[PDB]
Image: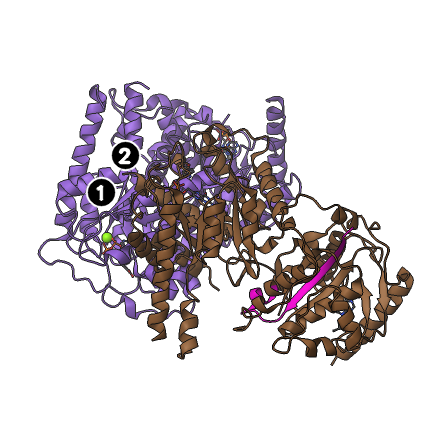
Chain colours: A brown, B purple
Amino acid sequence: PRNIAVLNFGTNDKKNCVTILETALYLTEKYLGKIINSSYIYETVPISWIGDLIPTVENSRYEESEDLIYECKELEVFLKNEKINESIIREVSVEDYENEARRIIKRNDEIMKKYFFNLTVVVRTFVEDPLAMLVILKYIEQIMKNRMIDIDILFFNNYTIFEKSISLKGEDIYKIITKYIHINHTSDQNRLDIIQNLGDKIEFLCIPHVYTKYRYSILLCLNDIIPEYKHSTFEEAIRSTYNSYVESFEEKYHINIRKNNKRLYVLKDKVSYLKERTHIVGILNVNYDSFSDGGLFVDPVKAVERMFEMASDGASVIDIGGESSAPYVVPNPSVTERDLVMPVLKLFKEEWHKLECEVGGQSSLQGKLQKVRDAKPIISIDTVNYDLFKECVEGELVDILNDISACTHNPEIIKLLRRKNKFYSVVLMHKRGNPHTMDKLTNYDDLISDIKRYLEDRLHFLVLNGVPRYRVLFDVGLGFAKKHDQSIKLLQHIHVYDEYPLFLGYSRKRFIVHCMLLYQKNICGGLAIASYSFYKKVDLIRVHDVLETKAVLDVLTRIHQP
Amino acid sequence: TPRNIAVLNFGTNDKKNCVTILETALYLTEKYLGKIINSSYIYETVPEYIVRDISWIGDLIPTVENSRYEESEDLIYECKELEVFLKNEKINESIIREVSVEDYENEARRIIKRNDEIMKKNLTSYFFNLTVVVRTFVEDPLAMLVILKYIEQIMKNRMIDIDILFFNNYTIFEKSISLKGEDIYKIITKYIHINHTSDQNRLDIIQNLGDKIEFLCIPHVYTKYRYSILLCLNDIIPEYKHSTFEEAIRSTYNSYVESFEEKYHINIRKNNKRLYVLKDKVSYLKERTHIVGILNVNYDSFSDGGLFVDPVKAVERMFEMASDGASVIDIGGESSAPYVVPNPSVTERDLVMPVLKLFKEEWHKLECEVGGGAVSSLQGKLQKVRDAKPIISIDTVNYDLFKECVEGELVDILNDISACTHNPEIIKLLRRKNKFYSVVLMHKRGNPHTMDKLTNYDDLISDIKRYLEDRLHFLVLNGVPRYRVLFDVGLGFAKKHDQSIKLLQHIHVYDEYPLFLGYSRKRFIVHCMWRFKMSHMRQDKDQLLYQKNICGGLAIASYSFYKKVDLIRVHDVLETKAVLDVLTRIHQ
Ligand SMILES: Nc1ncnc2c1ncn2[C@@H]1O[C@H](COP(=O)(O)CP(=O)(O)OP(=O)(O)O)[C@@H](O)[C@H]1O
Ligand SMILES: Nc1nc2ncc(COP(=O)(O)OP(=O)(O)O)nc2c(=O)[nH]1
Ligand SMILES: Nc1nc2ncc(COP(=O)(O)OP(=O)(O)O)nc2c(=O)[nH]1
Ligand SMILES: C[C@H]1O[C@@H](n2cnc3c(N)ncnc32)[C@H](O)[C@@H]1O
Ligand SMILES: Nc1nc2nccnc2c(=O)[nH]1
Ligand SMILES: Nc1ccc(C(=O)O)cc1
Ligand SMILES: Nc1ccc(C(=O)O)cc1
Ligand SMILES: [Mg+2]
């Protein structure tokens, strides 16, 4: 049986925050087991070589399967604080653990008495003890190098461990790494300097990490993934413990603990503050039969001129579609989804690579080239097709999977979202049926609750199969198996996603005009919804009339500046 | 002989014909009693019991006998009788017998106790309520009451009811008054040239008017015990404290409000609402955002110039606009835009008249097709048309033009961008016999060529609000109804762009008043930063930039919907309407 470890990841670098954490995740999963749950990233109050690291890292002596999983019996057992495996390392009693914990916390309090980006993860580990895991985590750190990256073990199974005075020499360390890693012995590549001094970075071991119930940041992350867990060291479960921290703090100091401590999501390479902006997603139908667009952008050169336009016009994201999903549509049978889309993506990249070479020949050469890729519009593909999406992430042609129907069409597409070092974010929309039948499928016992419940289960599936929680965006699918009164109701109750990253697509849909040559009327109705969306703090809105949506939000933003 | 100050309370049950009924009653009242020098809002109140045909009204106005007295219609700036009244000091000695405060209270509480009993045994509508201050030439409260009974009868749910709430500082209770026709005649004919002819008289009324007067009671029995009365008087005499009152009006209103909420635990304001009036009907304050459609009939307007000079086009445009959702249309003959020089070859008046008259000519052809058997009965069909007709506001500061407009029944609202300061005389034109007119007081400084230079305020938000409130006090003193006076902060007029924005930011200070805004196509919008077509946009100016200016427009339109602005004034009616519909839908 596999063990369960819960880890904590820390950095101080905001600029590079994602690349550092995700690189540290890649390597953890590699040398330790599958990552089967994760928190969001959290901003809390107390790299030009990183790519080169990946094809030089040493392989693991354990290979886990790439297969999708739907369950994890060990996780279910961890969570009940029940026994999975005899502890190799000596356990201690709760009373001795809390004595020797509380001593280290008062001493640490004394020394210090003279932002952080965070993440919890759950690992289904093939490592047999805590100590070994710890030695492996130190290795990964040094391979990179509390500034840079910090990985701590919070819970390893249900064990209560406390070991002072651990001294490990270059022999001990070697014996432990090479039980788990194929280490390179060769002169022209090795890390045997590192392995030799890795005992200097370990003086003691202690599960649970004993700041676990005493640090908001930790509780805050653990609250996303193991709210019901109650280690024996704890007097109440993580969510109850969280709640007794927030409450006490807001009672004692009467400031909102939420104010400085913020949830973050990621789209591409940088962190976003959840709910703190409404980005624009420019639409680009590259096909012969979309309502409102068909055929305008089939030619790759008109389709690329247009991307460049919306980018300029204000859109943060661009969302390519090769095939309509609109009511009673019959996709153009003369050219496929893939044939339409590939040239246009491929043309975009080549056009951006001419841009980058024309710039290549602040104010320096890197200063100039960093301003160019620092405004590259994010590219989001609107498909459900394994083989096309594969071809996009293999050629470096997209950043975001927009799977309408939440990766239920072919769940295997989920495995392409993590590619080695490279992660990719995903939009899970709600919908039923297909274009001819969706209208007819509108019975819900509890429209609002049911749909939230649908998306939440899809999320649990994706995080369990190793997609980071902070890359998953929701969408209620306005117009997709809703009547117009239902579509409007979903907007009315949009406050139920107030804890989640949220993406909406109203643009040009029929329900808009149901509120009232009259394309004019529908676009304007849209701009209203954009205001509503602004005030509801929707995270991303997906629209065709970028220039005009921009105008709205500029005005709305200005009015609401202190 | 100084004049007396009386405070009257008007009350009706008929919501559809509400405005006409009260404004008919204010006309007769001013005519026979004095000058109206102050007024409250109208309020929709829930009846306090326990402590629709008017097609004859118009033809009553010119047939009413004259007052023997006559006030000068000159503008006034003060009323000493009032000042005095407000300190509960004496004006004139009471002809009628006064009574001690303790005897007064005793007799009142019997009348109230007995009314409660009546109504307890008993057990349909709301009450629309207005209060008014009159500087009066009637020498005593009884004679006034007789003139009020006369007025009511001249008209006759309870259709109209007019009571004397205060008459000077007097404290009076006459328990059983008995006036025969002779007595009534003596009293009315001292103040009115009554017709004496067989084919024209009201001697059947005058003779029996006594039946309608059983006692006399100043202050009114219920003055301090009805929210609806306190609610009104809080507008007009808040600081007053009679001898019967343990504290002033405002203190007493807040006492009432706390007591209510600290008992029945509901908000008293939720079910008693402030109304305002644009033309012929009540509008519930803050309950809606209406769209005002801009019509510039001149060669020099910053975005419309030269499009609507031809009357036929300009009149089509007014039909398009009403169709597209505009509740009011605002015709403007001269431009006030920055640095503009108005075309000196044709006059504001020349431009606006052929239009306003054509439109009337046209609308009347509509009614005649409908009536005829083209385009609910006859009465039904024809009522619908008139309810459909757009309100007309005229944007000018010219006495001679507004005189002409009003004289021909061509407009319904003065939109005076100078807050009626260019020519204060224009105020006397807001009230013409039976017919009253609503007015929009906007804040500007300077003129199109100097406004931009006049942007030093000590306190922008509060200075503009003071100004507007002073302009309101001046109009209400000169007899314009407060429910017809609308505020506008004047965006872009003698404000820097940051200052226009700021005014929007603190627009909540107008949370108590009717509010009119015009952001449309102004400069400050763009300072913040299946196809879209602008319409009714000069081909001369920046096409791409005004796409952005118009759509920023729509953002304020949304913002305005949320802040509860009463009227927005826009070029893009179709679009603004689209936004308002959707937002409306989302919020049911
Ligand atoms: N201002 C006033 N002061 C004293 N008595 C008054 C008065 N106005 C009316 N009355 C008296 O009130 C009696 C009933 O007349 P109405 O005014 O019709 C009662 P109402 O209208 O049902 O109640 P309300 O006056 O409280 O609105 C008459 O005998 C009349 O003399
Ligand atoms: N996440 C998400 N993606 C979407 N993609 C397409 C459309 C339909 O819009 P459009 O692209 O204009 O039409 P077509 O499907 O015909 O391309 N709607 C959504 C949506 O609501 N949510
Ligand atoms: N009450 C009020 N009336 C107004 N009239 C005209 C203009 C200017 O707009 P427009 O008519 O388009 O320009 P011009 O004055 O050049 O006709 N602004 C206002 C305003 O803000 N408030
Ligand atoms: C930098 C210091 O942090 C300690 N450290 C890191 N993670 C853990 C854990 N889960 N338990 C105990 N100690 C830990 C190392 O032992 C080192 O001494
Ligand atoms: N609120 C209210 N109450 C009343 N009670 C009796 C008579 N009139 C009225 C009236 O006009 N309004
Ligand atoms: N793909 C879609 C396109 C349009 C609509 C809609 O108009 O309701 C719904 C789905
Ligand atoms: N009448 C006016 C027209 C325009 C502006 C403005 O754009 O600032 C101000 C006043
Ligand atoms: Mg004008």
Q: Is residue A556 above or below residue A104?
A: above
Residue at 79 percent of width and 75 percent of height? A171
- Which residue reaches farthest left? B345
Q: Is residue B183 above or below residue B487?
A: above
Q: CA distance from mark 2 to mark 1?
A: 17 Å
Q: Is residue B115 above or below residue B224?
A: above
Circle on res. B406: 1
Q: Is residue A53 left or right of residue B480?
A: right
Residue at 30 percent of width and 58 percent of height? B522
Percent of width and height locating residue A553: 41, 55
Callouts 2 and 1 close, C-beta under 8 Å: no
Numbered circles on residues, count = 2
Q: Chain of mark 2?
A: B
Q: Nearer the viewer, residue B298 or A158?
A: A158
Name the quadrant containing residue A139.
bottom right
Q: Is residue A311 left or right of residue A16?
A: left
Does residue B29 appear in the picture of this structure?
yes
Q: Nearer the viewer, residue A305 or A490?
A: A305
Amino acid at the residue labelled 1 = Val
* SS type, badge 1: helix
Cβ of mark 2 under 8 Å from ligand 3: the answer is no
Q: Is residue A270 left or right of residue B551?
A: right
Circle on res. B389: 2
Chain part drawn in magenta: A1-21
Does residue B566 appear in the picture of this structure?
no
Q: Chain of mark 1?
A: B
Is A13 one of the magenta-colored residues?
yes
Percent of width and height locating residue B223: 54, 40
Is B581 one of the magenta-colored residues?
no
Amino acid at the residue labelled 2 = Lys
Residue at 75 percent of width and 72 percent of height? A174
* Same chain letter for marks 2 and 1: yes
